[PDB]
Image: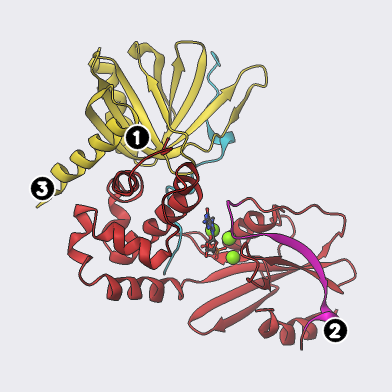
Amino acid sequence: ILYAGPTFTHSPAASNLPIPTFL
Amino acid sequence: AMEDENILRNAVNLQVLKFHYPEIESIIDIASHVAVYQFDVGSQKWLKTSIEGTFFLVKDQRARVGYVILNRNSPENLYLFINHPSNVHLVDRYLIHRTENQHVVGLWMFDPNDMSRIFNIVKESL
Amino acid sequence: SFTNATFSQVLDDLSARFILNLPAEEQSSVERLCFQIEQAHWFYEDFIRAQNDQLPSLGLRVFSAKLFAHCPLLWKWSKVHEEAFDDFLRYKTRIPVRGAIMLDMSMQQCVLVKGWKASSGWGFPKGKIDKDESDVDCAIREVYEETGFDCSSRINPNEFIDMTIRGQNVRLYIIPGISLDTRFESRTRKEISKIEWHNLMDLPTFYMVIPFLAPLKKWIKKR
Ligand SMILES: C[n+]1cn([C@@H]2O[C@H](COP(=O)(O)OP(=O)(O)O)[C@@H](O)[C@H]2O)c2nc(N)[nH]c(=O)c21
Ligand SMILES: [Mg+2]
Ligand SMILES: [Mg+2]
Ligand SMILES: [Mg+2]
């Protein structure tokens, strides 16, 4: 209903980021 | 009224950007919020750096295209140049920028439309 | 670097950093703008007033008034700022707050946290809910935020104490079996100064904990 923290504050965890083969 | 707010918005934005980096000339585009990450090679894992802020695709007085993140968590901002568009990759929900000196930065843009638009601008800008 | 920067240049920065380029989803209401004002205040107090000592320490209400009279987007609310700010903290004191009452393996001691300023009293690790996150995810987010301990594998969503202090709904999940050797440390920039255990018998049947002492003791005697 009411919130104190926006969505962009909940940035995805570091594990979510992709790992392409060249990394 | 919508265009008036955009005029005052870009005016204050540009004045603040010039306040931190006087070499900046204009603002090409803006993303509402971007979380920055760094991929640790040798550790083979992504590190979440606390650089969260507004994203400013800018151009300096020497025609160099770069981007500035006004970090909301600390005064340490992030100003990085894009010397060639083949260093930015649209992979999954993130952009992967390989800086000139073999640094891998991962930008997560809160707005997916901002991700696609920023990515397409960089791919067309050079 | 604000090492020497006028208060106007500071307010210009804080405008472009927290207010003027927000996502449109929360730039529609007035209270939602004031929550970013509170974020810009913590930045000004902790960071900007640390590179330029000449800048004054301002209360949240005073700082908001200066920034509302400064940023052109906010000029509409500058005259009715006292009433709009009254609506802001009237809004904030109604957000649901979730936390966890972490009991030890003997169920005779609990984990309490103390606020940053030395005057602030003790209380359970709790915090306000964010947009669209669940009550349990909120309790996990804020207990990890204020004590650095992850209770996701330990929280029981069916075992909680629901309270409505004033207009603020507070829910604290009872998590027993927390070992006394477990390490605690806050992961915020302020807000939490101390984290210690307290004997439940040593609590007053200062603290904002009293309301939960009646249900908690009945819950422990059951087990
Ligand atoms: C993260 N943080 C929290 N505080 C203080 O923490 C108090 C509660 O802030 P809160 O984070 O909204 O609490 P909650 O989510 O746990 O319910 C405020 O009164 C602030 O003074 C903070 N105060 C300053 N100056 N800077 C910060 O970064 C900061
Ligand atoms: Mg709290
Ligand atoms: Mg908290
Ligand atoms: Mg918080």
Shown colour of chain A: cyan
The residue sitting at 54% across, 26% down in the picture is B38
**Any magenta on residue C197?**
yes
The residue sitting at 35% across, 16% down in the picture is B82
Task: State the residue in front, B22 or A18.
Answer: B22
Label count reads 3
Colour yellow, chain: B
Quickly name the residue at label 3: B4
For the N terminus of chain C, the image quarter is: top left
Q: CA distance from mark 3 to mark 2?
A: 65 Å
Task: State the residue in front, A9 or C20.
Answer: C20
The type of residue carrying mark 1 is Phe
The spot of residue C71 in percent (x, y) is 24, 53
Quickly name the residue at label 2: C221
Colour red, chain: C
Quickly name the residue at label 1: B55
